[PDB]
Amino acid sequence: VYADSFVIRGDEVRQIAPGQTGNIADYNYKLPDDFTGCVIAWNSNKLDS
Amino acid sequence: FSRLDKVEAEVQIDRLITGRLQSLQTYVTQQLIRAAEIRASANLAATKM
């Protein structure tokens, strides 16, 4: 099992899903086509911001 | 493949591929029947020879 974590803009959460293009999902990191697993996304305003 | 996402569209082409094989299957079935009929006539032709 592999856990890959980071902090991303709250608007473009759906770009994490495979097949979505753009700049944060093309020029930074993208999932493979047959990816198995899933992502967890949540707000960080009190701590990080 | 080109217009929309790759993940969702696969069952779409699967629909297509199934139909094509189905069509092909139907065609070959008819040929067998015709062949059998022709074969019977051919055997009768042999008797006529």
Image: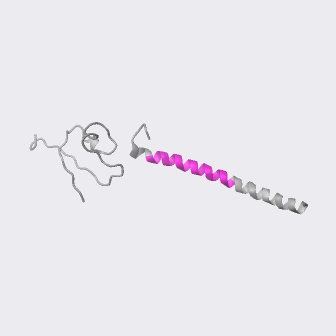
Q: Report the coloring of the rendering.
A: one colour
Residue B26 on the magenta span? yes
Quadrant of the snapshot with the C terminus of chain A: top left
Q: Residue at x 73, y 56 (%)?
A: B33
Left or right: B31 as drawn, with respect to B42: left
Give, as a single range, the part of the protein colored magenta.
B10-29
The residue lying at 36 percent from left, 52 percent from top is: A34
Type of secondary structure dominating the magenta stretch: helix
> Above or below — where is A1 with respect to A48?
below
Residue B39 placed where, x, y %? Answer: 79, 59
Q: Residue at x 57, y 48 (%)?
A: B20
Q: In the drawing, does residue B28 fall left or right of residue A39?
A: right
Decide which of B19, A34 is in the foreground and name it.
A34
Quarter holding the N terminus of chain A? bottom left
A40 drawn magenta: no
Q: Nearer the viewer, residue B18 or A42?
A: B18
* Image coordinates for residue A32, horizontal then vertical, percent: 33, 49
Residue A22 appears left or right of A10: right
How many marks can you see?
0
